[PDB]
Image 1: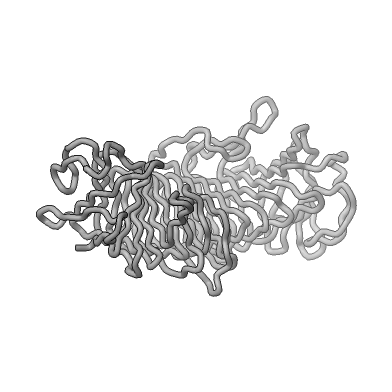
Image 2: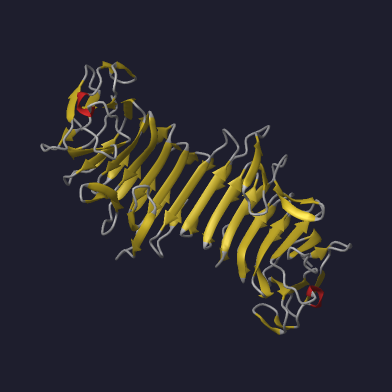
Length: 234
Length: 234
């Protein structure tokens, strides 16, 4: 059971189909179209995980036939925000599929995220954020990696998606092949808008060095490091 | 004598001061402010090279006191375009200084460019183009790396500038520390605007792989590879 929802209102319904693939019936989107899901644990194993963003029944790639997600109330998410609220880091070793209506996908975990052979299916954009979402008056205002020195790690088996990819962390350590339509990596201690515009930056008390080994199979790569002094090694 | 001007109208006056530092009195800018300099050979050694873009006499960093460049006729270049028109590749092993009015700097050499401990002083933007400039009706229209498989190489001693940096080539092989305000690397077989907007791209007949080893000390890095299939290894 890699994914364990929070007990409260923003905990989605989580189950599994024969073979171990996890199925997540994401919570009702708010009026902005954001499904804000909170978790005590968020990990994807080799059998993968399916996030049900469907308004009609149909065939998922990883978990077979599923009904429409009743939680949606006829209103598919524009953004599936997965927020780890505990101190547990995340490990992604398999595919995350959005079943139904294609959406943006975010995993935020300020304790650390590791991706080793992970991928994202039917996402327009997927973002991995070692940091927290920022909310004002119940609305998403952006993200923060301030005062955080934890790591976004990408292992030897890499990361694949047909969509856009954002990698957001105090520091990144990547050792595998990253395949994506576009890759954006933002490092350092920053605050961000909803769309990962950098709004502010702070100088870390100690060096925050990032390391990119391996190939990046993408037509467009951007790397922004705001940690004045700290570098990007390739 | 690393730098040898073309014999014609666009060949600048090239000399040297005691110690071997080369001094280039760039040609009269056109009405767009472009000083279009043509060369049989263009190489910068450890003593460096000073491009005289000065309207008044003064002190250069690398070559001591110089007069204003008489060729300017009171009209400093906005862009110093250095074009190698022969089949000779370029090696840059030292600093290129713009003396006088800060300008944009371009070196175009479709035969190949190698930079090992090179740098750029008093440039707002410096671009290394393994490719040719494109001219229509006497005006600069952009650049081309089409039908070219040659290499932009950066060696163990790296490249330093306080300004923006563009690296434009069919393929790039970098093994050292690149320090710049911003780094833009565009690889593949492309046509470009004057400002390195990609206007067209072609699929190369064979793979054009680029390799980035070493650190990139810059707050903003962009890598665009249009060679569908070919990758970027870090």
